[PDB]
């Protein structure tokens, strides 16, 4: 008793490529979670470039959880700063200060 069986199957579905704004969202001690596109603090740059095709000339909103520490915001800033990003909108924050 022996026979070679197979599981043939195929499905043709659409694949639209719409355009939408870039919105960042972080939570916990330090965890990035984009809309249906979760990432880490390590692949944050690589992933970002893979999604925005490496475009730092786009107004991206930086949404940081209310449970973020000073060290976290200091790392993300210094990281995105050295990695470019010269146009990052500050969500829920439009106030300036100097002294």
Image (cartoon, helix red, strand yellow):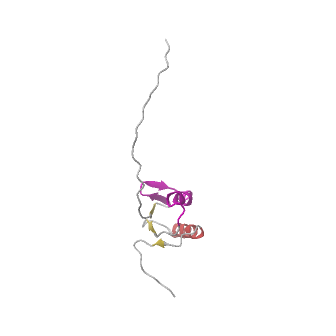
Foreground: 98 or 69?
98
Say above or below: 93 vs 45: below
The structure residue drawn at horizontal position 41% and vertical position 75%, both measured from the top left corner, is: 93
The structure residue drawn at horizontal position 46% and vertical position 70%, both measured from the top left corner, is: 59
Specify the segment rendered in magenta.
Answer: 30-55
Q: Quadrant of residue 65?
A: bottom left
Is 16 left, or right, of 29 in this rendering? Answer: left
Say above or below: 98 vs 59: below
Horizontal and vertical percent position of residue 10: 42, 35
Horizontal and vertical percent position of residue 85: 54, 69
Is 31 left, or right, of 81 in this rendering? Answer: left
Horizontal and vertical percent position of residue 64: 45, 66
Count of number-bearing discs: 0
The structure residue drawn at horizontal position 60% and vertical position 69%, both measured from the top left corner, is: 82
Horizontal and vertical percent position of residue 4: 50, 19
Foreground: 3 or 38?
3
Any magenta on residue 16? no
Q: Residue furthest right?
A: 82
Say above or below: 1 vs 78: above
Foreground: 67 or 52?
52
Q: Residue furthest bottom?
A: 99
């Amino acid at each position: 008793m022996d026979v070679k069986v197979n599981l043939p199957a195929s499905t043709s579905t659409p694949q639209p490529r719409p355009e939408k704004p870039v919105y960042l969202s972080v939570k916990a001690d330090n965890s990035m979670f984009i809309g249906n596109d979760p990432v880490t603090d390590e692949t944050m740059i690589t992933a970002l470039n893979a999604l925005t095709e490496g475009k730092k000339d786009t107004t991206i909103f930086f949404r940081a959880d209310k449970t973020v520490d000073y060290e976290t915001l200091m790392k993300v800033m210094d990281t995105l700063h050295q990695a470019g990003y010269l146009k990052i909108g500050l969500v829920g924050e439009e106030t300036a200060k100097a002294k």
